Amino acid sequence: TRQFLIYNEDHKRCVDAVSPSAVQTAACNQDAESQKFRWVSESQIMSVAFKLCLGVPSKTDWVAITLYACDSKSEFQKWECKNDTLLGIKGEDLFFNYGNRQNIMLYKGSGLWSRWKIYGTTDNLCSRGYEAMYTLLGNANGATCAFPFKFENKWYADCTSAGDGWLWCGTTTDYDTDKLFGYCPLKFEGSESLWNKDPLTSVSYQINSKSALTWHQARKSCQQQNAELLSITEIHEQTYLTGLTSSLTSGLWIGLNSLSFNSGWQWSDRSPFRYLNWLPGSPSKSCVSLNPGKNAKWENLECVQKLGYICKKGNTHCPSQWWPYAGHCYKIHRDEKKIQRDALTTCRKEGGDLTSIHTIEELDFIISQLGYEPNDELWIGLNDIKIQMYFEWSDGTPVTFTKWLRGEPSHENNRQEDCVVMKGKDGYWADRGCEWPLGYICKMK
Image 1 (cartoon, helix red, strand yellow):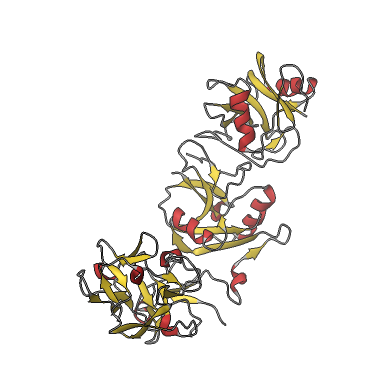
Image 2 (tube, rainbow, N blue to C red; image 1 turned 30 degrees about the vertical axis):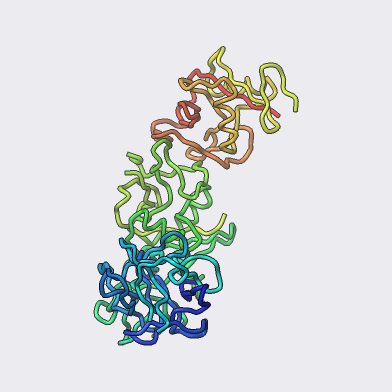
């Protein structure tokens, strides 16, 4: 809910807008539209009944707070929460005050008459707060809703079904002039028809090809829909997404990025990066685009490019020299360096396997308790021997966690099979060819 009632505990009364020149108080009534308010920017509180913003004529003491036409550049319409429930103008020690019983006033006192809460709760007004709502479909290419907006010479404060029940908004204040609109990312009858569902996995995908947002704007649009940018974690998922996007050509943002400075490629939804499908030549630009014109393969671009995007909604005894953690025994070998398959065999001769890693806590145990050194480079069990570009663990356990080094995974089109190693001060992983003599990390039950 975006609409709240401004409440003062001490008087047990609520702000009520009577006219554009009168903002009084009255007995609280949630069924009275004149008492409902809403944020429309980082700093502006707007009346729902009148579609006018609360403001002041000057930043001076004891002036009347009345309703002004909303202006995102007006210093006199910007409100911020101070201390806790203190509400005051931006940049001054002047406060939203209950006023003399003989209209709401801007006053210098910070007493109980200047502390306001959202009716029905115990949180300040800034708790609801304004979040930009990126639009879906429409002609505005995913631009943000503009509140308030004018449609057929009426003012609208929230998303409307005015003019099937689909909720929409104008992305500029005068929709009657600019004719720019989009649909709101809210639940309504028919909202789920914006999502395409994979019958097999029950995961829903939303393809927003008409839009043109930056990578970060795209990430916000999915997250405000209780989703996240597309992560492609398995061969079936890529196959389905190739089918959905066969009839498209323009690039679409997906969640694969390398924006974290100490680590490499990762999905924004923290899914494991175990399936690769780069376009020939990539990765040569820290954000990844899916190119539906080239069979839905991936290429990395500058994160400020304006593209479409895809959202995704859904999901106690150890031998000698072996050390325990979480019901398993681990050991690092450095004596005789072996290639990956010879190391795989030696772990199995010893009763275990090349190590799998499923949680970050398990990764931390290896780099700090097993004698691991920062200059090391050790085999682990992740590999794509069977299917190129699809990493699996040699012990058959699921890949639920990946921590790639900066600049990793590297060059997969330079070789025919990829084994991965553990190297660096953080124990992050890097893939490489398998015919290299190296140390290795074994793990057993």
